[PDB]
Image (cartoon, rainbow, N blue to C red):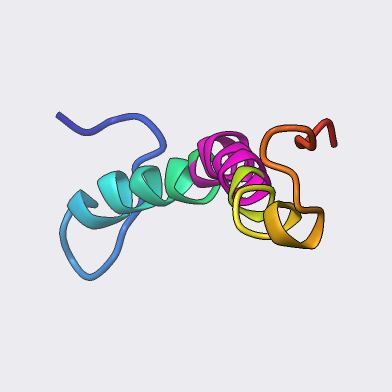
């Protein structure tokens, strides 16, 4: 059912702007939440752990002696 913030596209009520503007509402915001929180973290750890897993090993000749802590 439509009624809240109802718009008008062509000649019908607004079945597109309704869901489409709602899907975009979280797609744009909701996408910046987990994207940066979840991915921003995964890339922060997965990237920090991989760099400290195949570089300080030879470059530092040490296995776990060196970690992220950044």
Q: Is residue 8 magenta?
A: no
- Residue toward you, 50 or 9: 50
- Please provide percent x and percent y for residue 37: 61, 34
**Dominant secondary structure of the residues highlighted in magenta in the image:** helix
Q: Residue at x 69, y 33 (%)?
A: 64
- Residue toward you, 31 or 52: 52
Q: Residue at x 69, y 52 (%)?
A: 57
In the image as oriented, which residue stretches furthest toward the front? Answer: 61
Q: Is residue 32 magenta?
A: yes
In the image as oriented, which residue stretches furthest toward the bottom? Answer: 10
Q: Point out the image quarter for the N terminus.
A: top left
- Please provide percent x and percent y for residue 39: 54, 44
Q: Is residue 68 left or right of residue 54?
A: right
* In the image, residue 36 above or below residue 12: above
Which span of residues is magenta-colored?
31-48
- Please provide percent x and percent y for residue 23: 34, 46
Q: Residue at x 36, y 51 (%)?
A: 7
- Please provide percent x and percent y for residue 13: 20, 50
- Residue toward you, 58 or 40: 58
Q: Residue at x 61, y 57 (%)?
A: 54
């Amino acid at each position: 059912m439509a009624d809240k913030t109802i718009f008008n596209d062509h000649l019908n009520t607004n079945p597109k702007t309704n869901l489409r503007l709602w899907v975009a509402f979280q797609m744009m915001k909701g996408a910046g939440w987990a994207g940066g929180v979840f991915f921003g973290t995964l890339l922060l750890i997965g990237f920090f752990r991989v760099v400290g897993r195949m570089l300080p090993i030879q470059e530092n000749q040490a296995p776990a002696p060196n970690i992220t802590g950044a």
